[PDB]
Length: 283
Ligand SMILES: C[C@@H](O)CN1CCN(CC(=O)O)CCN(CC(=O)O)CCN(CC(=O)O)CC1
Ligand SMILES: C[C@@H](O)CN1CCN(CC(=O)O)CCN(CC(=O)O)CCN(CC(=O)O)CC1
Ligand SMILES: C[C@@H](O)CN1CCN(CC(=O)O)CCN(CC(=O)O)CCN(CC(=O)O)CC1
Ligand SMILES: CCCCCCCC/C=C/CCCCCCCC(=O)OC[C@@H](O)CO
Ligand SMILES: CCCCCCCC/C=C/CCCCCCCC(=O)OC[C@@H](O)CO
Ligand SMILES: CCCCCCCC/C=C\CCCCCCCC(=O)OC[C@@H](O)CO
Ligand SMILES: CCCCCCCC/C=C\CCCCCCCC(=O)OC[C@@H](O)CO
Ligand SMILES: CCCCCCCC/C=C\CCCCCCCC(=O)OC[C@@H](O)CO
Ligand SMILES: CCCCCCCC/C=C\CCCCCCCC(=O)OC[C@@H](O)CO
Ligand SMILES: CCCCCCCC/C=C\CCCCCCCC(=O)O
Ligand SMILES: [Gd]
Ligand SMILES: [Zn+2]
Image (cartoon, rainbow, N blue to C red; front, side, top):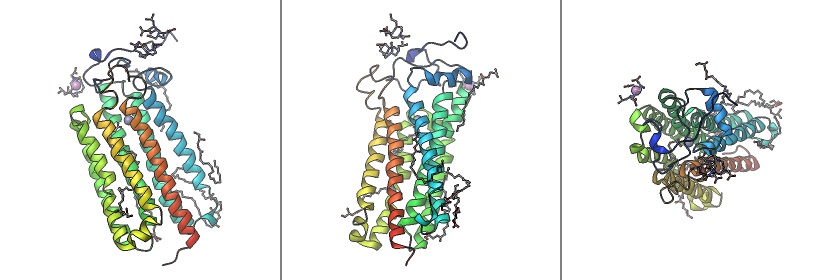
């Protein structure tokens, strides 16, 4: 098309608001204050191609998975309205996170102001992913006891809202604060260790590891700590500058870790429900 033609550019030519990873040396999209060109650029090769498509493709996937769940027969659930509301909040959190992300990774190169607004929606989406993922997990983990279930819900929501308020600070988006983000969100998700200690302290290592939770929760902490480590350390683009530029750089692998992470997490709480059903609502 002879409308909105652009070329990829090296890092040095990017304005300071687009310059974020000095290991992605070429393949950058230039500032294009046209969302027409921005959304058309989804069908182009560049540093954000994979970022766009992993969370764009992953967003339609959670959208389908969250629609199909809503239309599940109500005999499957002990309390289908309640049980569907808890999963619903996880699914919305998963959908919003991926949407804010693929939208931001798309309209990113548009302007400084636009990238500034959508990056704050992008960060905020991570916090809503963690918050929402806790809701069905606490519903089944603290099923027969609601004093911790209520407290831990407020704890994850008070922490998540703080993370979301800290995401509005413009320093938080700078590449000097990259480690601070990987710690802020990593801390948010790892704070689940509080209710894990508490659950284990009252059910015991038998009632906790027999029911898969311990084996699953560890893999989840692996995905969380390995994943955040990649983002903050910029691996592998640190070891192969200008070679891992279009495919397989850290932000791209991190997207895969987020979609995979939210799938492992869904399959986990979709087991706590398959189990709570095989036992009914007894206390
Ligand atoms: C003559 C080349 O310098 C032109 N070529 C540059 C890229 N490489 C090599 C390089 O990086 O210099 C050539 C390989 N090429 C097609 C093929 O190999 O058949 C892929 C498409 N590219 C995209 C682009 O760069 O805009 C078209 C322009
Ligand atoms: C300049 C861009 O318009 C090229 N662009 C499309 C065509 N290429 C070329 C190929 O087919 O070999 C595909 C693979 N390519 C290798 C390479 O070109 O170095 C990746 C890196 N290039 C950066 C660069 O070209 O300097 C970005 C991709
Ligand atoms: C001043 C800097 O420390 C912070 N600033 C970036 C400055 N750029 C400079 C450039 O990169 O050319 C100007 C672009 N523009 C504003 C304008 O129209 O002057 C966007 C809004 N600004 C507001 C401001 O200018 O303070 C946001 C942050
Ligand atoms: C959660 C998903 C939400 C939907 C995301 C968007 C999907 C559809 C995308 C549409 C892109 C259409 C192009 C939008 C083009 C408008 C911007 C533009 O360049 O305007 C120029 C002038 O009007 C001003 O100078
Ligand atoms: C559209 C409403 C359908 C209602 C079905 C009612 C029965 C309950 C359904 C349970 C889940 C069935 C398996 C479907 C599980 C979701 C997978 C999905 O949709 O992935 C999206 C990708 O294929 C595309 O990117
Ligand atoms: C889908 C994204 C996740 C966030 C929630 C979105 C809000 C959904 C709002 C309204 C949906 C109205 C219809 C809701 C339909 C759910 C009940 C249903 O059909 O169960 C199958 C049973 O009939 C079998 O016994
Ligand atoms: C922010 C997201 C919150 C969740 C929104 C979606 C909630 C799910 C919607 C409807 C579930 C209704 C379950 C109600 C089950 C009642 C029993 C019945 O008679 O079932 C017949 C069914 O066909 C009725 O659905
Ligand atoms: C983006 C999403 C962010 C997280 C939103 C958090 C909202 C929390 C509020 C309500 C969650 C659904 C509660 C649904 C109502 C629960 C009532 C109940 O009987 O609870 C006892 C159970 O624990 C065991 O049976
Ligand atoms: C996005 C949600 C991800 C999952 C939910 C929250 C994640 C919580 C974070 C970390 C929990 C990791 C648990 C790792 C295991 C700790 C429990 C423990 O001490 O078990 C004793 C047994 O090993 C004895 O055999
Ligand atoms: C959902 C289950 C876990 C999935 C993997 C999560 C990885 C660890 C979480 C946070 C650390 C990375 C912080 C990224 C902040 C900037 C957001 C971005 O643009 O990607
Ligand atoms: Gd400015
Ligand atoms: Zn991202």
